[PDB]
């Protein structure tokens, strides 16, 4: 069947270049136009580059001309996208598409490669107590970071909220709803685990 | 060049007919081919309508493409909507050198009844105040659909600087979201009012916090 | 002079084709034909195409057989000294090929030019 396996992205500091690759299978490679589609978090689909059957026609919008360069290799049946001088506004998911020119639509879509551009540093989180009790994990990178109550004592009642970028750093909160006769009659502990820095922080909530 | 405008989100019940519009800025929409794509959260997009009305093999016959020249728009009609249709829908058109896409329409299928959010406020921690830093937490839960816009008010005035809000994700049975407000240690205790407003389905739910 | 077909509407151009048909004035979903026929013993001609939109396929290096499969010109015409040229005048795309010498067998090929929903293809036939 038709498959568009794409790879070659990840996390890197701004200014560095990156070349995405998309190997195509299941169809004659030098007989169909191909394109790259970008989707940023919350901005929707955005076309960035397009190449013809053997590179006879090249297309970019007036927003990334000169900075991006689409390429094609027949000996490897591969579609390449060289993104030089990566900026913070380039963090998005990229897909490679086989489109049909005579019908003006993308027939097949690729797998999807995430590209994240940030000057952020791999640093340990900061845990704070919130008095329903809460544990606030602020200023951490990278993901994931988990928050368990009493080292996994009770499963039902704990709700952990997703993270959000504040100043190029993730931040989340984990809450639990407790009855009246339990708190503050019982000691409550919060264990926050971050595997990247291998940091386990234990906190307590007392008013 | 032209711009394709699409509504942000539309809500329709199960087993009904929905029509998604796609208006063109400049030029007649009938002159260029229109395509419709379905993009699910965390997955690659799939082609739904390739020509103006033709659909490819694999798309159910309930999906249909049409062109309304009276309003210079493209309509995607879905009869007997199923739960699997909850995804984003994108309108595309090519015009000699540029592939213009639409804004995108988040289709939400109404299966569960309407629910209003429940807010949980959290003031800055004492250890953070010893650190001279203020972070206010606003937890929103038990709300459907995900159409929710949050805001923060300091003593009644809308404060925009230092607001970080995540997106609603599927937890429990309804959506769930969090919001955070940055504030200076001394600027927090200066004014004795900080409210977290949540606008969902017309209901503007509010909850306050005071340093007293 | 170019023994080809011109589908562009730009009145000012440094290229001069033997046949010009404005594609912007024809009906939608209609197809225009522009046949080219060469029948001389030895050729030293330049045959090309000026399309105001897109070209299918990447033409004159790979061509469309007279749905059908895409072949390559160097093997269809069977001569390894075919020269290729290109140019761009705004949105207009000019693709040309110069041919020198004889040809072992009469051959024919086709190239499509599409702008919006309008599409028109030109055919080239070289008799040995």
Image: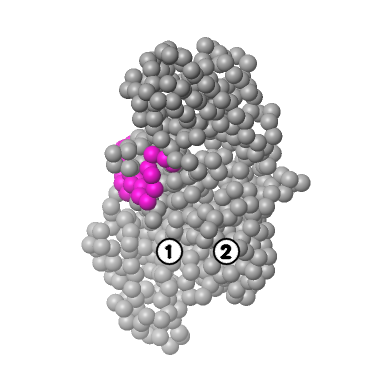
The residue indicated by pointer 2 is B60
Mark number for residue B80?
none
Nearer to us: label 1 or label 2: 2
**What residue lies at 51% left-to-right and 64% top-to-bottom?**
B168
Q: Position of residue A62 (x, y in %)?
A: 50, 31
Q: Is residue A31 magenta?
A: yes
Along the line of sight, the residue nearer the viewer: C109 or C10: C109
Please, is residue C14 above or below residue B139 in the view? above
Q: Residues within 10 Å of mark 1 (few under 14, many from 20)?
A: some
Residue B188 pos. (x, y %): 49, 57
* SS under mark 1: loop
* Coordinates of residue B82 in the picture (x, y in percent): 58, 69
| Residue A162, disc | 1
Taking the view exactly as shown, the residue that stands out farthest to the bottom is A181
Please give the range of residues in magenta.
A6-32
Q: Is residue A134 magenta?
A: no
User: Callout 2 environment at 10 Å: few (<14), some (14 to 19), or many (20+)?
Assistant: few
Note whether B156 is above or below A117 in the view shown. Answer: below
Image location of residue B34, percent across then percent down: 61, 46
Q: Chain of mark 2?
A: B
The CA span between labels 1 and 2 is 35 Å
Chain letter for mark 1:
A
């Amino acid at each position: 069947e038709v498959q568009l396996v794409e790879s070659g992205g990840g996390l890197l500091q701004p200014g560095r270049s990156l070349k995405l690759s998309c190997v195509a299978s299941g169809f004659t490679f030098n007989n169909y136009w191909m394109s790259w589609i970008r989707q940023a978090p919350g901005k929707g689909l955005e076309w960035i580059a397009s190449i013809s059957n053997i590179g006879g026609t090249i297309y970019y919008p007036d927003s990334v001309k000169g900075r991006f360069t689409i390429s094609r290799d027949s000996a490897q049946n591969t579609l390449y996208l060289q993104m030089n001088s990566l900026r913070s506004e380039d963090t998005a998911t990229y897909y490679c598409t086989r489109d049909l020119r005579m019908s003006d639509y993308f027939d097949y879509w690729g797998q999807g490669v995430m590209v994240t551009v940030s000057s952020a540093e791999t640093t340990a989180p900061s845990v704070y107590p919130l008095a329903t009790l809460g544990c606030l994990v602020k200023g951490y990178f990278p993901e994931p970071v988990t928050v368990t109550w009493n080292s996994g004592a009770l499963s039902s009642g704990v709700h952990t909220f997703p993270a959000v970028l504040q100043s190029g750093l993730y931040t989340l909160t984990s809450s639990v709803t407790v009855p009246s006769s339990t708190w503050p009659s019982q000691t409550v502990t919060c264990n926050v685990a971050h595997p990247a820095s291998s940091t386990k922080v234990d906190k307590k909530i007392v008013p | 060049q032209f711009v394709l405008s699409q509504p942000n989100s539309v809500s329709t019940n199960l087993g009904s007919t929905v029509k998604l519009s796609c208006k063109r800025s400049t030029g007649n929409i009938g002159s260029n081919y229109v395509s419709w794509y379905q993009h699910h959260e965390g997955r690659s997009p799939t082609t739904m309508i390739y020509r103006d009305d033709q659909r490819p093999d694999g798309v159910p016959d309930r999906f249909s493409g049409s062109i309304d020249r009276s309003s210079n728009s493209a309509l995607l009609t879905i009869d007997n909507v199923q739960t699997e249709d909850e995804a984003a829908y994108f309108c595309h058109s090519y015009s000699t050198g540029m592939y213009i896409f639409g804004g995108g329409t988040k289709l939400t299928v109404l299966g569960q009844p309407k629910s209003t959010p429940t807010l949980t406020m959290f003031p800055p921690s004492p250890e953070e105040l010893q650190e001279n830093k203020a972070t206010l937490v606003c937890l929103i839960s038990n709300f459907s659909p995900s159409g929710v816009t949050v805001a923060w008010k300091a003593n009644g005035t809308p404060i925009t600087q230092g607001v970080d809000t995540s997106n609603p994700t599927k937890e429990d049975n309804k959506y769930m979201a969090s919001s955070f407000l940055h504030l200076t240690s001394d600027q927090w205790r200066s004014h004795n009012s900080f409210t977290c407003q949540v606008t969902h389905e017309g209901n503007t739910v509010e909850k306050s916090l005071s340093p007293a | 002079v170019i023994h080809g077909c011109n589908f562009s509407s730009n009145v000012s151009s440094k290229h001069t084709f033997t046949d010009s048909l404005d594609i912007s004035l024809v009906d939608d979903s209609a197809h225009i034909s522009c046949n080219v026929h060469l029948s001389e013993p030895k050729y030293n001609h330049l045959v090309g195409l000026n399309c105001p939109g897109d070209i299918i396929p990447d033409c004159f290096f790979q061509v469309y057989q007279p749905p059908s499969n895409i072949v390559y010109l160097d093997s269809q015409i069977n001569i390894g000294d075919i020269e290729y040229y290109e140019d761009a005048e705004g949105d207009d795309k000019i693709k040309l090929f110069g041919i020198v010498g004889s040809i072992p067998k009469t051959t024919s090929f086709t190239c499509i030019c599409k702008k919006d929903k309008k599409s028109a293809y030109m055919t080239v036939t070289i008799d040995s």
